[PDB]
Image (tube, rainbow, N blue to C red):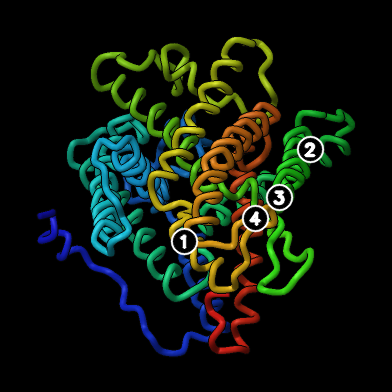
Amino acid sequence: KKLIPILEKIPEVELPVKEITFKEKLKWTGIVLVLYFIMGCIDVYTAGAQIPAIFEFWGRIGTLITLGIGPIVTAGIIMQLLVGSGIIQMDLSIPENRALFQGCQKLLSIIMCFVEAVLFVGAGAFGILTPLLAFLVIIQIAFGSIILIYLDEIVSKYGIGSGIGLFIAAGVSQTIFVGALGPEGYLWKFLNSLIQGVPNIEYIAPIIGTIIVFLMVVYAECMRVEIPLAHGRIKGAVGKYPIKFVYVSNIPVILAAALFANIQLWGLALYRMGIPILGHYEGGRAVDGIAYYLSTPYGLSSVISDPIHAIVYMIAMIITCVMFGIFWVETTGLDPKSMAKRIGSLGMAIKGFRKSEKAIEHRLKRYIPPLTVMSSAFVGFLATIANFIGALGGGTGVLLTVSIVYRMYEQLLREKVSELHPAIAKL
């Protein structure tokens, strides 16, 4: 038995078995992309056209998407947590557990949709807690986030890549082009600073920071784990199959940084609305407590003035990553069961040896975890370091973006081709 009733009440998206042309999947995505950007341009209805100049610069918040992917990720965090620590053991295999784990997470996503909404205004994100206007706001806020949930479904079944991934990449990229070249653009603030005759290195600083990060992030994104393959019945050296050593722990790291997101928010929220359980904020963010020790130091320049803070964070992040990584294993992730015959059909057993199902199925179920762990541990490290360096858009985000974007290029390719041989939609 399960929460199937209300779960069956929750809307979904009609997936056509019809012809969805490349040109269409594209044009569709495009429509989503914009409605997004557009929402980010529109402010939430609130007489208090004031969000303390304090949170004003705080990424988003004040727009129709003040919550953004925030809830969606939170939810995913919980599930990975339960269905992760065995707390609620489930063997997805059957379409039951699969659609159960999913359908369920979705619902929670909406729960969290509102919870976060309230949690945001309750954290004093706007300033004027007019019980009436406060309610009104919450509405719009969490309802916009909802449109994303659905706009995601759309892309996820009518376009390319993914909503979330897009939205993320979309965000970061905008944040850059605007931050550096927009109205109050930074490249200008610097060039002008140069004309004014008082060369301000702090105006070009962040722009560099990014470049470096990008250059860096990409390098790592290139590394791969090549696994030589046994001839498909033939004879001699053949395959060399590569795996995206970094993109393995993508969704994972998104979940880690996401967790620290719900802490700083839940700390300040459960601060100016109760007891300082997590930490003493003051001044907007946290200056003490768990919250403090778990706050990313980036923005403009790297803060050396707190060595300990750094170390903790890094280690803190690292371990959180390994975690969701593993919790990405017990669940969905790379499942050898399938990898079994998929690799068997071609009859391409690894380069080592064993051209059998249970055979490769095993060498696979083995190699996996160390990989999954290694990868993440690294990523999370990188990301964290990419934050010390600090870059426009968000060191970490810039990372996700680079991956997301490239995995998106790949997607565009696998598509340009499947747009010829109407069959090989599994090779």
Q: Which residue corresponds to mark 2?
A: 208
Q: Earlier in the sequence, mark 3 or mark 1?
A: 1
Q: Quadrant of residue 8?
A: bottom left
Mark 3 → mark 1, Cα distance in angstroms: 26 Å
- Label 4: which secondary element: loop
* SS state under label 3: loop
Residue pointed to by mark 4: 353
Location of residue 393 (image quadrant):
top right
Comes first in the chain, label 2 or label 1: 1
Residue 200 rendering spot, x and y as whole percentages:
81, 29
Disc assigned to residue 224: 3
Read off the residue under disc 1.
163
* Residue 180 numbered tag: none
Alpha carbon of mark 4 to alpha carbon of mark 2: how far? 48 Å
| Distance Cα–Cα, label 3 vs label 4 | 21 Å
Callout 1: SS? helix
| Nearer mark to the viewer, of 4 and 2 | 4
